[PDB]
Length: 52
Length: 42
Image (cartoon, rainbow over all chains, first blue to last red):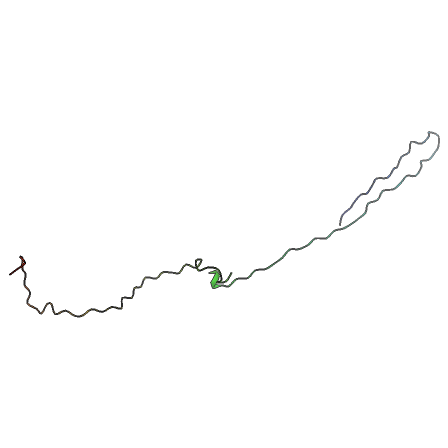
């Protein structure tokens, strides 16, 4: 699994220079998603004399 | 795979015998009276 940071939020706002507080902003998402892995296999035979 | 693939991939070891199987006789030569000629008529 791995992280997927989606979109940074809008944090600051350029407020007026009188108020004693900020103003909330939108958040960001991270979306911890996963993914699997496959396998590959097969076989093959032989005689023993017919290979010597 | 197994022997369904050509008769040319298997090199046969060539051994070094040689059967003859024929037959000669003995010889009555030494018994006969030896003699030596030089022309073609004596």
